[PDB]
Image (cartoon, rainbow over all chains, first blue to last red; front, side, top):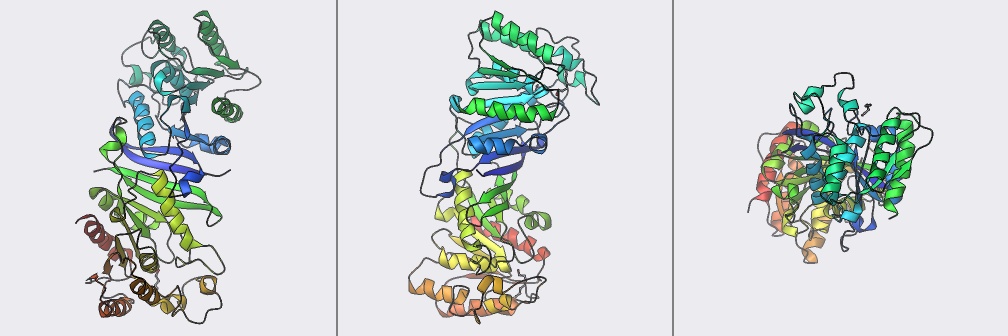
Amino acid sequence: GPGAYISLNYHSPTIGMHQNLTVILPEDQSFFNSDTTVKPLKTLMLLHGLSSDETTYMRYTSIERYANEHKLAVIMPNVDHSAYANMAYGHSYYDYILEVYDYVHQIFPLSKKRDDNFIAGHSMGGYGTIKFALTQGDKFAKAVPLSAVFEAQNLMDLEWNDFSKEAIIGNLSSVKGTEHDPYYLLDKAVAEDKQIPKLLIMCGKQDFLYQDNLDFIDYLSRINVPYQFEDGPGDHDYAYWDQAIKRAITWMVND
Amino acid sequence: GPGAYISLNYHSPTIGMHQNLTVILPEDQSFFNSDTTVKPLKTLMLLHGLSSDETTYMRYTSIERYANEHKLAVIMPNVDHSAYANMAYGHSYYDYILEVYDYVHQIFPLSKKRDDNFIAGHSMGGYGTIKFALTQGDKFAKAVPLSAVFEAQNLMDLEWNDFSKEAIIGNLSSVKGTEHDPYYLLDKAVAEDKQIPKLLIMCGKQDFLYQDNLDFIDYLSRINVPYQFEDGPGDHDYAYWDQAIKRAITWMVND
Ligand SMILES: *[C@H](O)CCCCCC
Ligand SMILES: *[C@H](O)CCCCCC
């Protein structure tokens, strides 16, 4: 039924500034009883897309209703225009996510088991999710990119309002074959026999990264990595991602 | 040293509604290392006065600055116009404070030791502080009423904007000898051999309640209860309580 909506602001030693962070914490009966041990909750790291921040998932979906139904803690950080990268000219936003994961597991009643921790996100956050799935596999059991960018050149060459490509990648004019390419990180993951989280890849059929998503899931089957692809009517809007994260949260908590 | 500013909104099972709550959580090095076990922080329960709520101590003082220098967590809840009582016609806001206490000790890295937990507050919060000090002495080692109300008839018969006495005490025609009388709770604490927390009572000398404060500390001395009383130039405003809460926070965490 109920839960806590928590808004944090702390000085980050990683990115060197105060930063906002919002956390959904569903209510457990352990939390109100002083004589019982706390039961740790499953936790979702939820990554916003470009132009969004730590507030927009709460504002534009009804995710806390979905999270309280399945008693899932949700962590929503803010990474600005970074594409979740340790930026060449800017903040160390790849490392910031591992700091956010470490902090809220130390301070909130969250379970540190691999089988209890998930990660998801949309657009840039979906591209962020597939980066951490392929590079931080022992931290997360399942990963759900929604309408992700899988060929990062489409995100880097995107002409978005005040978006700075050179701030992330520096003087490089291609991201193919580097730590920004999910195809390279996928190749390195199968090469080193690294744990890949359980993949649920969601994208609306009328999205523009739909064909971007079709290329990625086909590449996954050619290298024998299991996934689950759910399509259907949808565009690149919070109307899709509201319904998508509702089915996504139900998918991750039941196994 | 830096810290986290945390604002919670959860459905409270005690008062039967969603309620806002603010938390200062100073940063320890423990919080960012997952190979470290978390060292729990000292905790202060900070109670606002009449017409205020959970936001006003941050807005009108610099308490998070003072709390972070002394690594002290600060818990600031909202109790409306209740005078921290289980109201006859209203919410059970006495029990709510025990619920807030139980909730943040379970979900935040706070020390559950008696010598690490203090309680404080101004005006009506000073009335709440001395009510919980004399009836929950096992939960607090130090209690700091600032500019407080000790003669409960002065608060019940107060003509403040929209304040309702009968919502608190109902048809009662005097507070003496009841659970609303802090002098009565002091007698019952002495008689039942209940541990009285260490008291620091502060009131400015131009306050209306200065003579009210002298009557309680005079009575306190007459039944052989130790206290420390600090006075000086001060009035009934957040300018005095900003400077006083800095003095109180330094007093409570040392020795
Ligand atoms: C990503 O957050 C949304 C912008 C669309 C990117 C298409 C490459
Ligand atoms: C206390 O919260 C502020 C009002 C002054 C009360 C004096 C009886």
